[PDB]
Image (tube, rainbow over all chains, first blue to last red; front, top):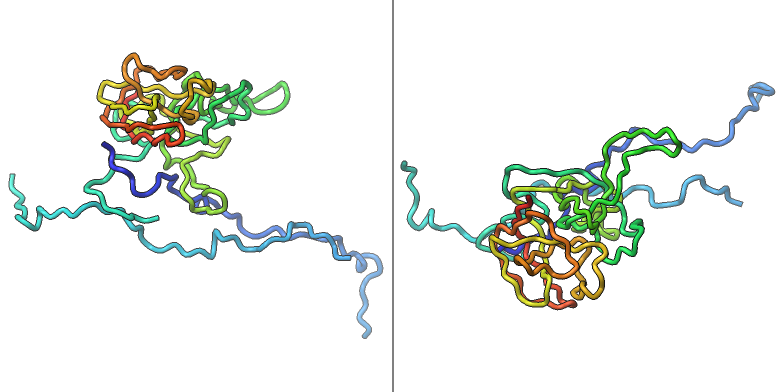
Length: 45
Length: 45
Length: 211
């Protein structure tokens, strides 16, 4: 008695539209550069 | 010799973005309703 | 994908949805896992929308020590539990995740551990119903509803029905092993053709009144 549905039944909203992406990116850091803290810096050349 | 990456190497951009969704939605249609053109209507009562 | 045909009228509704507005009772719950089910748990189901779930414990408490915070009255339900909890429904509540890479592929299956809306009673609910036998059946206004449990024995489940599949029988004809939803009635009238274990024709969706 029910008319056969044309589209296959499915959950309506794709997940991609229900995501909030946080501002910015987290950059991967490295070891500190502390040669200037030890022996200073000099410009001679 | 190469330093081991912190993150897993992968294709950067997801298919989530860079994906244009066409405006409007196609809607399933039914058979033609033609009594309004064969005999017309009159809003009475 | 799009309409490959044109029918004289629209379908009255899609399974898991509400057609008639009136007194209704629904509760939230978590989908759990048939694997987590301690006992054998024979009947297997993919958390389909139009299926009748069963209570399988609570997950109110949070933490891992003695002082636990009861954050919410949370129900932890399984697809074919004997203690009927409610028929899953309202597909618009959930998010489509796709199926096997195709993120836009159609899917009526809720992932494990998700949250669903389980109608305990409704004036009108579109449900997929099945045949409890291999013969053709006619369901009318005065017809009852019984859902397949998780522990339905292989001898009783000859047709290989899904885990929480609602069947739909006639007074004094409940397929064996099946457990009945009390006060559940088939409102609209339909016909199911003869089926076999391999074919298992998907019974046409039906308006049902629960309690």
